Amino acid sequence: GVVHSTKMHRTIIIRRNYLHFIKKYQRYQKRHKSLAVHCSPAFDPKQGDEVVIGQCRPLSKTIRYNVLEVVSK
Amino acid sequence: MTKTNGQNAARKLVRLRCRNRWADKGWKRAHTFSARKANPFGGSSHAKGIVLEKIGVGAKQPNSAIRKCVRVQLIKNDKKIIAFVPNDGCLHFIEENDEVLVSGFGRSGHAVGDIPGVRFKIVKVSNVGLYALYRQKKEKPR
Amino acid sequence: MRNYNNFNRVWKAPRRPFEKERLDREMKLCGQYGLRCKREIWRVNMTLSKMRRTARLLLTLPENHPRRLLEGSAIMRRCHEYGFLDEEKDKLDYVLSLTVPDILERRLQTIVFKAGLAKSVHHARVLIQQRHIAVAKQIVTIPSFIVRVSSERHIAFADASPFGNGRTRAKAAKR
Amino acid sequence: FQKKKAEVCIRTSQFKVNKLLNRKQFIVEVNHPHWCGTVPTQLIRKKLATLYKVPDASQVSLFGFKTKFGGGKTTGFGLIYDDLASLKRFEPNYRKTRMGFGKARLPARKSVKERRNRNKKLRGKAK
Amino acid sequence: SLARAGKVKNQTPKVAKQEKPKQPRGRALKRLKYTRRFLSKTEKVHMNKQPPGK
RNA sequence: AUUAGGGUUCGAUUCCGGAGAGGGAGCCUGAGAAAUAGCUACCACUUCUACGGAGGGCAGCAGGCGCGCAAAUUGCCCAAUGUCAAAACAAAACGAUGAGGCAGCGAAAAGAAAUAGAGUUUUUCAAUGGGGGAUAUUUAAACCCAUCCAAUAUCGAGUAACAAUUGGAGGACAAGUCUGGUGCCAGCACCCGCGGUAAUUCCAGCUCCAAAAGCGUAUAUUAA
Ligand SMILES: [K+]
Ligand SMILES: [K+]
Ligand SMILES: [K+]
Ligand SMILES: [K+]
Ligand SMILES: [K+]
Ligand SMILES: [K+]
Ligand SMILES: [K+]
Ligand SMILES: [Mg+2]
Ligand SMILES: [Mg+2]
Ligand SMILES: [Mg+2]
Ligand SMILES: [Mg+2]
Ligand SMILES: [Mg+2]
Ligand SMILES: [Mg+2]
Ligand SMILES: [Mg+2]
Ligand SMILES: [Mg+2]
Ligand SMILES: [Mg+2]
Ligand SMILES: [Mg+2]
Ligand SMILES: [Mg+2]
Ligand SMILES: [Mg+2]
Ligand SMILES: [Mg+2]
Ligand SMILES: [Mg+2]
Ligand SMILES: [Mg+2]
Ligand SMILES: [Mg+2]
Ligand SMILES: [Mg+2]
Ligand SMILES: [Mg+2]
Ligand SMILES: [Mg+2]
Ligand SMILES: [Mg+2]
Ligand SMILES: [Mg+2]
Ligand SMILES: [Mg+2]
Ligand SMILES: [Mg+2]
């Protein structure tokens, strides 16, 4: 996904974009989803960067993923 | 010149059709509770009532006749309607405070024929079919 | 509750109730084959439409399609085994040409009449219903029985009927 | 038509020896071309005993006969036990009641249930 | 004025039903019609042509 | 369900998943319950009483009362399919089971199929079921189905009264310019329209048409 916000402490919001297909009209829609991810101090991502995340045990009310790799800009 | 055509334009097409379906009178009547609340039967096909009085309704032009009808009050919700007594001389089978079964007149709430504002019809009185009494296949109880 | 025995429907009414040409054509068949009601004709209509619908689907597929090979041979085999088509007809396109009289010819009622065991097609109907006809030593009382070509020569009078070694009006006359 | 007498012919199929229950089980098929009605099951019992050379006709059990439509045939099921004692041990009570030797009917189930519920209110010698 | 209900029904002179032999039922009836329209007796075809009168 | 294709619509209901046991909370035992044919309290209803007191929960199976346009027997059985368990079956010696199965009621719906046939000049022949029975068969026991009306030995159609109905006959839409009655009345008519003294449409009689052990009507919904 892509980094959407970095205002929390050691937590970021990422966004996933995809196209959904409607069978009746034979055409697509644009949709998106948001996730909260824990970000270790070993990384320094910025808004707009692309990250790779992995699933882990529940860490808070909304966090279920950890950042594994950052691809800058 | 009249439709969007883009490959990724499904959201526009979906919202367009949803909005324009409310202009169809048949579709709107099916998805709105206004019609059911005003319908005396409340969505049923038949209803029972108590005869209040006998009245005569004049036909509409260019016909000329006195149509024999009856005023009944529905048991389930205490509403007043007017119902038609179909066949020849069948008004003599009905007395006040009798219990009758009422059905529709065939056009789903619209008025039928030259009878002004009548959309109901008597089909059974005192637990015996009205048409059976007309054909003398049964006798009026009590 | 909790009963899983299946059942379905075998006939459908025509969608124009009063068509002058159709009414006359059907009254021809009832008199010619001695049927009881229009429902017996409409039953044959549904079977033909099922066969023709299947054939159209297969003929769309390319010839080397596996499903066309297996189903195509299966339906042709069934048509030959029941006499709906002669063995000369081999391609799958000939099944689309089946007509209503083609199937009515194979009824047991019309088979026995043409075989000489009955004076008329109405005489054949009562004989079958009265347990006089046997197919391969088996009594059959269903006029709509569809006989196979390999079973045509085994049709004869039953062994328990007076007409062939039975009788174990005359029975009541002598008492 | 040729008037004759009544004669039956019996065949068996799917024969199997079952040593776990000391018996042999098979399908019995009988042809009765000129029989007047249905062949009573005791008559088939005698013929089967003779055909399979069993010392006592009481040690063969038959049940569930269906007459073919059109007449002249009947099919059922049969069991030949090794001895009379084995039959009286492994046989359902209703099948041996048909053959003569079986327990009597216990009282109606409704009466038993009523007594059981009455006793649930008591304790000790009363029960 | 509801007093005239059933005027014509009660005013009609009464005519009794006429007894006749029964007709065949089922397959026999279809056989009867087939021979009337086709077979027997071979433009417009009239099924219930009535005698003249005025 | 409907059907060229694309679609529209229904899914309380047999299998899978969730939730509840009048309403609302709380809890003990237990591997497992926030359990209700377990316990505790309050609210709403309600039963017995010697007046001191003590009880209740069918949205389990049958049954009632109400409500409604609307839905069965206070039946038989553990023989089959399974569950529990200190338990194979038998022998003094038969585990429970309204789970489940079997019958009764039942034109929701689905399949097969009678109400005659062949002749001769208006009378002659055969044939068969509906029905009555049976050494018997089926079944846990009955019932239905199937077999038979001598194997020495076994009832029965002529008006075959063992008698087919429901809607129609101006057009849409198959089928009468028939004969009586009525006279803008009574009534018909989904729509267009009939009826005011010669009614192809009302009320009837004849004849005919369509589907047929089925056929009309009302309300929804799919195609059109
Ligand atoms: K923590
Ligand atoms: K109940
Ligand atoms: K059991
Ligand atoms: K039942
Ligand atoms: K039926
Ligand atoms: K007879
Ligand atoms: K007239
Ligand atoms: Mg559901
Ligand atoms: Mg509900
Ligand atoms: Mg469930
Ligand atoms: Mg619970
Ligand atoms: Mg309750
Ligand atoms: Mg425990
Ligand atoms: Mg609870
Ligand atoms: Mg309870
Ligand atoms: Mg005291
Ligand atoms: Mg409680
Ligand atoms: Mg009902
Ligand atoms: Mg024991
Ligand atoms: Mg039960
Ligand atoms: Mg049950
Ligand atoms: Mg009759
Ligand atoms: Mg009989
Ligand atoms: Mg049964
Ligand atoms: Mg008339
Ligand atoms: Mg016409
Ligand atoms: Mg209509
Ligand atoms: Mg006149
Ligand atoms: Mg008309
Ligand atoms: Mg539509």
Image: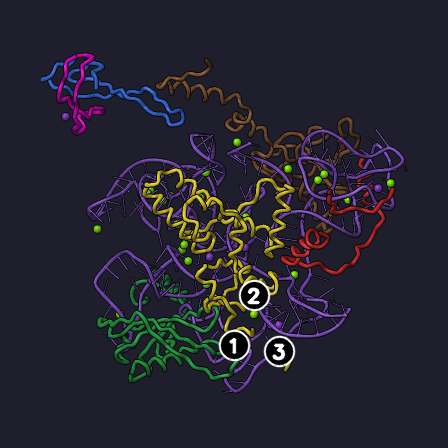
Chain colours: A blue, B brown, C yellow, D green, E red, F purple
Secondary structure type for disc 3: helix
- Determine if the C-beta at disc 2 is less than 8 A from ligand 6: no
Residues marked 3 and 2, same chain: yes
Q: How many marks?
A: 3
Q: Nearer the viewer, residue F221 or F55?
A: F221
Q: Nearer the viewer, residue D46 or D112?
A: D46
| Residue A47 magenta-highlighted | yes
- The amino acid type found where label 3 is placed reads Ala
Q: Residue furthest front?
A: C88
**In percent of the image, x 35 and y 38: which residue is there?**
C62
- Characterize the local packing of mark 2: few (<14), some (14-19) or many (20 or more) Cα atoms within 10 angstroms: few
**Residue at which label 3 appears:** C170
**In percent of the image, x 86 and y 44: which residue is there?**
E53
**Residue at which label 1 appears:** C165
Q: Position of residue B29 (x, y in %)?
A: 54, 27
Residue B108 location, quadrant:
top right
From the viewer's perspective, is residue F54 above or below residue F79?
A: above
**In percent of the image, x 24 and y 18: which residue is there?**
A15
Mark 3 and 2 residues: CB-CB less than 8 Å, in contact? no
- Determine if the C-beta at disc 1 is less than 8 A from ligand 6: no
